[PDB]
Image: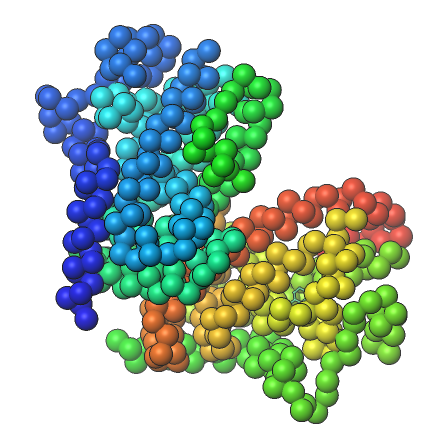
Length: 257
Length: 252
Ligand SMILES: O=C(O)[C@H](Oc1cccc(C(F)(F)F)c1)c1ccc(Cl)cc1
């Protein structure tokens, strides 16, 4: 009944708060004035870049990309911590635990990145910086294009006006897919996702009573995530040929495929 | 209220029955609700092919699939016309919705013709095995992704009355690129989504979160379609060079 599903919802939200520093709520408070204390240094061209390094401490195109990838790997750690708290997750076959994270983290990374973005740019270094979209778009060689798809998603995704309590459940749903390739035991995964889907449905009805079919519309966005991730990986294998200079982390090229 | 959404559901189902000759129900009766009036002819290797009565083989098989797709597109177009509100949209947008919708719909309906072992062909008269397809240079792999989708998709045990609404949902996607007026499209999809939700609760009271699970499958359709196109342009360099058919590849 309703009551159990709210409990699951609260539990998740708490794990989310504990696993992710930098909530959407915090992000939105930074992006929308809201503060003297919280206001970000803005990077929009080469020079502001250099100041940033002096103030909001951490080829340019290479450094920026590598930094993105470094932050991704510590996001994966946060996501992994979160997953552990999803009821039932740790009781799964460990092979499957790994498979769910393997295929889930990117989709989740892009979901959360949307909270850090608006149409004009994206927060960086724990929200202290903000790097414009145009400045990203202008980078050398094939780097001038890695972030754009993610901005397009973000703008659409953020139109749903979800809050952290909505996102915590949606993220759990993503992890517990069961369509992931190479899963040994799909049934227990679906059973868990089933509950998550109910928790989410109820959560959205309560938290967005005015919003017709938000549940549906949110699930439809998973199509968009998947396309982003496949674009990213294919982009990646180019910035690996050409940039044989480039290296990837022990959490990453394992995930990639 | 419920009542209006059932009306929309019935209306759609009726249009579906009129627009598509071979229903899933019929297909299922042929594939296995057997003891039938007529079993399909089975193609499992080169020879059964030839009798199939009813120019590299791999080429002909692919081209045939494409010819059948094009007449499916006509059926789908007829169906769309009956979706309430569709014909009232900007015509540019009507075209855009069909342009980007038909493939997703084609793979959805193809699933009704498939099981893990193969696929019905020529109005259900034939059946071509998966292993025979799998064995065809790059042709031996075009159908495999679609079998994987089909098996998963068909696990949802949807019937024609479920599929009719789902298909409408697909068409009325306002994330298609180049749409002029997204709002009316979403408004229509919104209703369709309700009709579907109710439809699945009533037609599958046993199955928890079927709505959710069905929408999740759209992720799979979209990947399939992008794989297909990104396979297709490789066909462009095998053997369609010839020009004993300028009007055909024009049509197809
Ligand atoms: O010939 C057929 O009956 C069938 O055609 C198709 C092809 C695509 C789509 C559809 C349908 F409209 F039924 F979805 C039928 C078919 C299916 C697979 C292949 Cl490899 C060749 C031909």
